[PDB]
């Protein structure tokens, strides 16, 4: 398990949290020195917990599938909450088994499903440490009408930062304020599977992608990634989704 406390949080402590998170995940090997997540894992071993505490010292435990960094649900005291989808329903057989009340959220963890539930797209949902604190509080008290937005903040602040150094850096920089994520940040999130697949193909194709991955750069400019020498591959992506889990 790994923990992150908002009270006393700093750019450095957020980085340490993300490093601990990445290191809590088992990997098959490294491709271009990037950890390759496992194809599959048996029962309980497939999940890990992140204990997140807000400024007010209230904690939620978040269940994460270690093969894909997908969040399954979370626990607040003795009430558990799981996404309305197959993966989460399976996770519930193994995690938070003794919760006294088990709530099924009215949506899956899919970005589009969450955005529709939140009534806002990621471009307009603030991130940064104070945002993560607000999200934790919202989830701890389960204010239903704000939960989808809180989950979008939570997912990006844990899974997306773990997957990309760039995202980790952006979120960790905002300690006493919030910010709206750039199209580049969102582009990274949307293309994690594609990038993961192409990097693995490149490893046995002389660094060449079979199919280009189109991303939006810092200047909102559209760019096409086609090989393992790109900066996104050499200096950003921190975890790779196993090709076996990519359709």
Image (cartoon, rainbow, N blue to C red):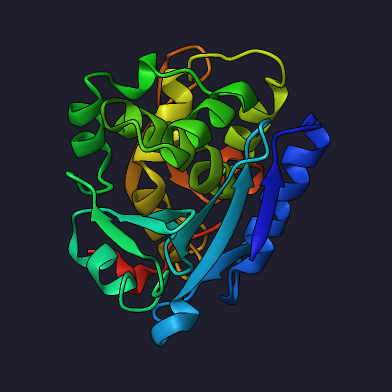
Q: Residue at x 36, y 38 (%)?
A: 142
Residue in front for this viewpoint, 76 or 20: 76
Q: Position of residue 197 (x, y in %)?
A: 38, 59
User: In this rendering, does residue 201 appear at all?
Assistant: yes
Relative to 40, is 13 above or below? above
Write down the quadrant of residue 73 in the picture: bottom left
Residue in front for this viewpoint, 92 or 20: 92
With 228 as the anchor, is 107 left or right in this view?
left
Q: Residue at x 26, y 54 (%)?
A: 103
Q: What quarter of the picture does the N terminus occupy?
A: bottom right
Q: Position of residue 240 (x, y in %)?
A: 49, 60
With 191 as the anchor, is 89 left or right in this view?
left
With 176 as the anchor, is 230 left or right in this view?
left
Of all residues, the one furthest to the bottom in this rendering is 42
User: In this rendering, does residue 71 appear at all?
Assistant: no
Relative to 38, is 110 above or below? above
Q: Position of residue 109 (x, y in %)?
A: 28, 47
Q: Residue at x 61, y 47 (%)?
A: 52
């Amino acid at each position: 398990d790994v923990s992150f406390r908002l009270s006393g949080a700093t750019t450095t402590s957020y980085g340490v949290f993300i490093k601990n998170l990445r290191e809590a995940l088992p990997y098959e090997r490294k491709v271009y020195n990037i950890p390759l997540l496992r194809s599959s894992i048996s029962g309980s071993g497939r999940y890990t917990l992140l204990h997140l505490t807000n400024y007010a010292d209230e904690t939620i435990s978040v269940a994460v599938d270690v093969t894909n960094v997908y969040i399954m649900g979370y626990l607040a005291g003795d009430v558990s909450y799981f996404f309305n989808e197959a993966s989460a329903t399976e996770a519930a057989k193994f995690v938070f088994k003794d919760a006294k009340k088990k709530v099924t959220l009215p949506y899956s963890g899919n970005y589009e499903r969450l955005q529709t539930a939140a009534g806002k797209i990621r471009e307009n949902i603030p991130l940064g440490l104070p945002a993560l604190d607000s999200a934790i509080t919202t989830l701890y008290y389960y204010t239903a009408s704000s939960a989808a937005s809180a989950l979008l903040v939570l997912i990006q602040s844990t899974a997306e930062s773990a997957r990309y150094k760039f995202i980790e850096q952006q979120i960790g920089k905002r300690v006493d304020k919030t910010f709206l994520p750039s199209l580049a940040t969102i582009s990274l999130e949307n293309n994690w599977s594609a990038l993961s697949k192409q990097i693995q193909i490149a490893s046995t194709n002389n660094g060449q992608f079979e199919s280009p991955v189109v991303l939006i750069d810092g200047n909102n400019q559209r760019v096409s990634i086609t090989n393992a020498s790109a900066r996104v591959v050499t200096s950003n992506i921190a975890l790779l989704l196993n090709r076996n889990n990519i359709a």
